[PDB]
Image (cartoon, rainbow over all chains, first blue to last red; front, side, top):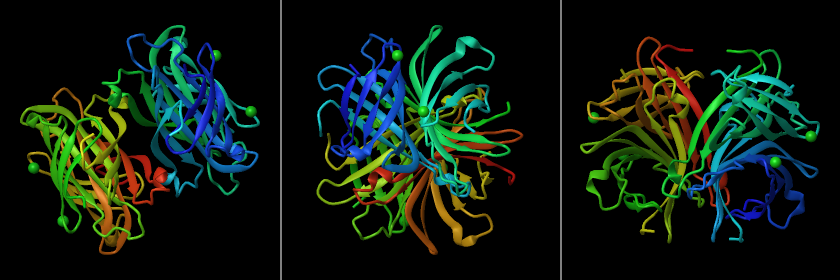
Length: 120
Length: 120
Length: 120
Length: 120
Ligand SMILES: [Cl-]
Ligand SMILES: [Cl-]
Ligand SMILES: [Cl-]
Ligand SMILES: [Cl-]
């Protein structure tokens, strides 16, 4: 249920393959339709989730370096997949930039993204 | 500078290899000296960081499933590596458990870890 | 624009007064229509926000103790008010429980709430 | 045990009064010894905590507006007080700036502070 394409509510999209034993691998495109905005992502998921209706825990990282861009930063998304009609991956994220020590206190942004199988 | 073993301040340790083009791969052991507490981790880092003194952005995920344990949960660490004498990886983390929809609001813990090359 | 009643998307509601010089005071009801679920809240807001279209920064705390309940915990909401038609207070929150030292690492939940002037 | 002066590990300090029924009121000084860096804070704490060794949950907000400064932003600290020799208030914080809608995704920084009764 995880393998495939997902869209957040703001114009990003990623493509992921969920390996049989817990690997996540794919590509994150921060601006739909812009190939210069595609970055590697890698992560993990629970490959034997509960069968009681609960979601499937997962996480992934994108370091914002590709051939076109280096933001000197990385985002991690932590969340759960919820299957069915209206499947979704509900996440909260942390975006850390490399900083000097004086600026470390402002290194890390927090937010949330809801991913769906259809565009907003 | 990232490749190798790191210890948080509370008794965990991980081992990571930083690939030339941004891959992080390794193992996270949640309780030092307990092999049943070793889990796969995967992530990304900025493989061309700034040279102005700033840290190197990175992130990784551990899904808490191995042959001995399934917590139906995953932690992502987001942070930066700071090299030199007293090298450290300073992070903030998100731990999401798979939940029912009614319990989703309590799915995700937040915290921080400081990793060093020597044990606390 | 802040003074008044707000509803999150999940069944809570609060009532706030925004004082002229930055005070927030009011009541948070975690379950709409249940008076046993009303708790004091107090906080602050920027009483001279930018006039360029940007939101108004604010935050508040509820300690989850009233005459009916003590969860030994407190939530802080940090966010911004955005006025107009479809006014909203967009927030992220931290819920810390009192814990033993051994359990401190799991003391704090994170999430988000969007408040509107009309019920979901 | 909460009433009094506390210092984070980076050069801030605040002064708080813990009211008998859960109020926190005081002043936060972001740069020790600089009176232009003093801002109102208000919050809540659990005024009947557990007696089993667990910490006392609390939170507070500072909106970063005073007579000298307006950063158009507010920080909330969520945490717990732990008494005894080496008393501490262990916190995680969210700092939200007022932003345009386009920039909302980058509105909120996250971090942590440990407060002690003695300066670092
Ligand atoms: Cl796999
Ligand atoms: Cl690589
Ligand atoms: Cl006021
Ligand atoms: Cl009081």
